[PDB]
Each structure stands twice: as C-alpha cells, then as structure tokens.
Image (cartoon, rainbow, N blue to C red; front, side):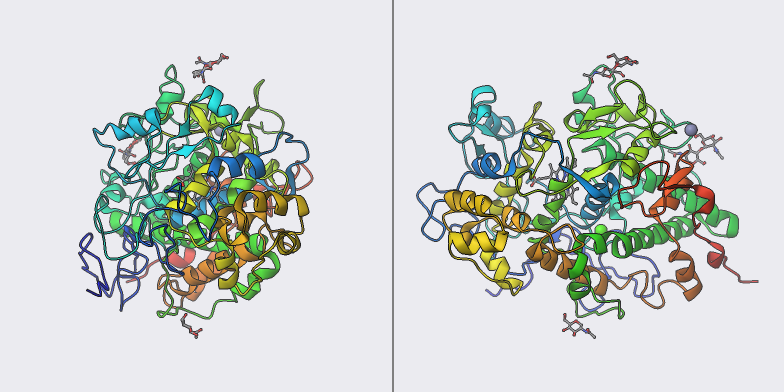
Amino acid sequence: SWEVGCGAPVPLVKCDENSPYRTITGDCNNRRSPALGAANRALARWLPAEYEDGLALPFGWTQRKTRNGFRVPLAREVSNKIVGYLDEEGVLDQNRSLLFMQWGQIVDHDLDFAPETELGSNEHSKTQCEEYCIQGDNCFPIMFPKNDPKLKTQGKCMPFFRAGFVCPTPPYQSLAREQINAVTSFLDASLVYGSEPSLASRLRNLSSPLGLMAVNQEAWDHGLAYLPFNNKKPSPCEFINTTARVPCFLAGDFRASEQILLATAHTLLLREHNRLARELKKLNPHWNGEKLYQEARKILGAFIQIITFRDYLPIVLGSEMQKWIPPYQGYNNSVDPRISNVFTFAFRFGHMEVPSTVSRLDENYQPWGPEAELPLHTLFFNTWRIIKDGGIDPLVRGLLAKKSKLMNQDKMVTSELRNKLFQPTHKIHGFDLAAINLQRCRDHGMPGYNSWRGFCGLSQPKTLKGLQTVLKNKILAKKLMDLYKTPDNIDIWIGGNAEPMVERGRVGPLLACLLGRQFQQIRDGDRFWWENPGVFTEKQRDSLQKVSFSRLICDNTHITKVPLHAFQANNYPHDFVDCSTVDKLDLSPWASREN
Ligand code: HEM
Ligand SMILES: *[C@@H]1O[C@H](CO)[C@@H](O[C@@H]2O[C@H](CO)[C@@H](O)[C@H](O)[C@H]2NC(C)=O)[C@H](O)[C@H]1NC(C)=O
Ligand SMILES: *[C@@H]1O[C@H](CO)[C@@H](O[C@@H]2O[C@H](CO)[C@@H](O)[C@H](O)[C@H]2NC(C)=O)[C@H](O)[C@H]1NC(C)=O
Ligand SMILES: *[C@@H]1O[C@H](CO)[C@@H](O)[C@H](O)[C@H]1NC(C)=O
Ligand SMILES: [Ca+2]
Ligand SMILES: [Zn+2]
C-alpha cells in the first residue's frame, strides 16, 4: 500500500558500527538509515517526478500529449538552434586551466551514474532501436528534425536507451519511476576503488601484502604504472583503432576511458594510492595489506574532498559559495547525503567547458611532436594515444598550460561533443551530447525550468520579456520561446546553463543553488568527512591541509615544473615553479606506535 521502502535488491545490511573505514558500497555511513548514500539505490527526488502519464513516460513520448498545452520540442532541434556554434576562435576561458573542466568530470563520476537499462543482452532492440528508430519500452530514439544535416548522412534518429530504475528494470513499481545511482553518493574516491565488492577486489593486488592497486603488466609509462586493461569484449578502445588494438582501462568507474584526459586523471589517482601505500609500509612495516589499502584509500578520499571543496567549488560557485556551503560545523546525521536526480543534470554544466582540441606538450611546455594538438572527437575511448604516444606526462602538461572552454550564450557546446560524440556499440563519431542531455532530462522526469527557479527562491519568468531579463539576452530568450513556447517547459539542463554566470563563478544563479545545496549535503551528511572530528587526528588534518593538485602531479609523474594554483589559467614559464618549492603531504602523523 504505502510502499515506504522498495528494497528487494541489495537487502543486505551487515554494518560494523566500530569500523574506522568506509564500506565500498556506501552502506553504514548513516547509522539510523544505513542505506543512505549507498550505491545501487534510487537517486533522491527533491521535487516529485514529472512524467507525461504521471508515472514513467517522458514528456515528448506521445506526439499528441502536451506539457502545459504545448508540444515539447525535439532534443536535437534545441541542440541545433541554441547549443551549436561554428567559430572556436575566442571561446576559451582566460582564467581556468583545462584541469578545471577535467576535475569537474572526476568529481561528477565519484558522485553519480545512471546507467542505461540492460535489456540489450542478446536482444534485437540493442541494434533494432539504432536500425529502425522505433520508439518502445527502453528505446527512446532522438529523432532528427527535417532540416538536420544528419538526416542526410546518418538516417532518421540517434539511438537512445532509457536509464535503469529501482525495483526490477523491465516492469512496474510503487508510483513514479526512480532512476538508479550506481555509485556512492559520498565524495569518497569510489571512482578509483569501485562502488561494488567484486570490482573493488578485482582492482586490488592481493598477490602482495602491500595494499596496492593492480597495475598494467603489459605496458609502462617510463617505468610508471598504467591502470590495468579491461580484458572484456567488445571494447570501444579497441574499436576506434583495430591496428593498435589497445583496450580500455579498468578503473573504479565504468567511464574512465570515455576520453583520454579522464583516463589521464584516473592514472594520476591510481599512482597516488600505490605511492601512499608504499610510504605507509615504510612508516608501519607491521601493517598488513588490508590496513595499508584502507589507510591509503582514506587519504586519497580526503585528497579528493579537499581539492573539491577548498580549490574547485569556490571558482564554480563564486559569490554563491558562502550562501550554499557555509564553513564546516561538523557531521549532521539528519542531512540526506543522497545525490538528487536534478544534480546529475545540474553538474552537466561541464559539457559547455570542454574545448575542441587536446594538446600534448614537451618538457618546455612546447608542442610534443608534429600532431601535438588533436581534435577532441579522435580521443573518445582513446587509450592507444597514451600507451603508444608518450604516456600521460604530455597530456598532464596540456591540462596545466591549456584553457577550459568558457560557457558562452552564443557558443554553448563544441561540435566535437554536439556532432561527433562516440558511444560504445554504435560505431560512429556522430552523436550529440546536448541532445542526449535534453532527452535524458525527460527520461528522468525532470521538473521544468520554472519549477527549479521556484525551488531556489528565484523569479519564474512567464513571457518573452521576463525570460529576456532573466537571461540578459534577447536573441537566446526568443529562440527558447520559439521552441518551448513557455519558460515552464524549458528543460532544466538548457535553462540552467542559459543563465549568465555569477560573479567569480562559472554557473548562473539557478545552477549555483542546485549544485550548492547538493555539495552542502554531501559534506554535512557524511560520517567520514575528512574534517569530522575523530576521522583523522588533528596532526593528520594539519598534514592534509597542505595537499594540492600540483604536488599530486610532482609525486606521480616525471613533470618537475607546475603552477601553484592549477585550476587558474597558467602560462609557462612565468606561472610555473619547481616541484622543490611545492608543499609535500607529510605522512609522519600516520606513524602507528604500540611499543
Ligand atoms: C570530453 C569530456 C566529457 C565527455 C566525453 C562527457 C560525456 C558524457 C556522456 C556520454 C554522458 C552520458 C549522457 C547520458 O546518457 O545521459 C555524460 C554524463 C554526465 N556528464 Fe559528461 N562528459 C564530459 C565532461 C564532463 C564534465 C567536464 C562534467 C562536469 C564538470 C561532466 C558531467 C557529467 C554528469 C554529471 C553526467 C551524468 C552522470 C550520471 O549520473 O549518469 N561531464 N557525460
Ligand atoms: C602485485 O604486486 C607485486 C609486488 O610488488 C608485483 O610484482 C613485482 O612485479 C614487478 C613487475 O612490475 C617486479 O619489478 C618486481 O620484481 C616484483 N616484486 C615482487 C616482490 O614480486 C606484481 O606485479 C603486482 N601485480 C599487479 C597485477 O599489479
Ligand atoms: C592506429 O594506431 C596506430 C598505432 O600507433 C597509428 O599509427 C602510428 O601512425 C603514424 C602514421 O600516420 C606513424 O607516424 C606512427 O609512428 C605510427 N606508429 C605505429 C607503431 O604504427 C595509426 O595512426 C592509428 N590510426 C587511427 C585511425 O587512429
Ligand atoms: C541538521 O540538518 C537539518 C536538516 O537538513 C537542519 O535543519 C538542521 O538545522 C541541521 N543542524 C545544524 C546544526 O545545522
Ligand atoms: Ca562516491
Ligand atoms: Zn620519464
């Protein structure tokens, strides 16, 4: 009847109350409700889901059924008319390095993943949805509007499969459909260690009692470790280049090889675990492998939290940072730490920060070889350009010395993502991440733009002129009104990203509120927050305050010249220092004395 808890899956609650370490699943963090923030449960609903039929059909599903009296426009038509641009000149962020973009993706992948339903195992609709563009069950194809050039070269649609949902994926559940978060809601390095026990063990080196993560046994980066290969088929990293046949990496997170700089960041974090585990073994030779793994895992989780909340979030939220994330006042076990469904769309502001090219730079921060700069689309599921072209150092120098794309109301998403995206099992560099995001907002039953404005205490524009004023842009407001016909129908991904950025920040007021609230909750609601008294000793916390992405690079690469503020736009050599001058993480406070 009430159906308070639909929890047939993952019923197991076997909580050690005493454990100084996190579970891999996120279970037991909250003592009163131990499933809160656990992986493989429903995304939180801050507002009730909004479906065409009130339960699970997306707006746009039934041609005849309006939203508030108007047909919702095709995701791809919004993408073409609003999100696309031609000229990559002038589009770079003069005050954010490319590392700023890349850290956002890292944090996002630690916090949330809504994987497509697996109803494609030995299924026709796996290829049939792509082949015949026929909407049904989990097939919700992105149809091309009539004037779309892709209609001329790529057929009628782009394939799209509905996200997985809680209480059996194929059939009906208690009231509205709730999509799954497959990773831990805590900011806990689940993207390095995994959110499931099987994966987390596969990633470990259990051959030695050294608490190490498994490393590649077939390839080395000038003696430095690579992630292991994912030896499974079919492999998109092999598909791109069947001559090189270099597989995807195997990381804590499914998505680690989606692009070369994400793979690069994952590689830095793995190196850091093993570095930490080796340093701890020197300090504490009596520590067994499990203890070394847990202790290094706990430090790397703290590293990710401190970089995120001290360095990253202030330059995302700008003037809104203090409003939404006041200085820390300790653990609040009444806070809901779960990632919300809306946050998983709010955080996609990163899509508008991705620039059109990636560079490899040499030890003078000068172009590395004759093709030093490459188009982003050639680097989707690309591991062979790492193994076979110079390792991660040239790409890390690019992350430091090159710039994020700046979000621009006239230039939102580069064609490298908007027309050339590669999706596994599709075979073409032909997808549109903007269209996918809009279709997914509808898949997840998102409330529209004005419902979220109301949620955030902001004005709800009802007319062209009101929207013009909110967006500070008359042409953008007119295009959105021509497509939507009411600001109430504007999908949250495009409405949030259309707002001009807050002072000293990189998102508008609506996104600052949605992101701000989520990050407040993941900090306040986390029993294992690095700064929660008892988690670390006061001396440990004194050491941890000195972490920086600059030291992470110095410690885990052959790079000896780094900037002191790695998320800022930094130019070589003026903004760069020797690793010598950069604070180290002093692990002496981890020395464990019994006798
Ligand atoms: C080249 C860089 C990137 C690529 C190729 C990429 C690709 C993708 C793809 C294909 C999806 C899945 C879309 C769907 O099926 O609904 C996605 C989701 C997402 N992306 Fe990106 N992305 C990039 C950068 C970023 C950045 C920089 C951020 C944040 C700052 C970000 C945040 C997200 C979030 C939060 C999701 C939803 C995750 C989930 O809950 O399932 N991405 N991205
Ligand atoms: C697991 O860790 C062991 C212990 O370090 C690794 O084996 C060593 O392998 C390296 C080759 O990369 C050799 O240089 C050393 O001589 C070996 N040392 C010892 C003490 O055996 C093993 O490669 C690791 N396995 C994985 C999958 O990472
Ligand atoms: C597939 O990967 C191979 C293997 O690296 C790439 O070949 C390199 O190709 C260029 C020629 O354009 C040479 O100058 C390099 O020295 C090659 N190395 C080797 C070992 O062959 C090839 O370019 C890739 N093709 C695609 C489609 O990505
Ligand atoms: C604990 O969280 C609850 C619910 O979010 C909040 O209302 C309360 O004020 C919080 N406690 C403190 C001390 O901020
Ligand atoms: Ca996590
Ligand atoms: Zn080297």
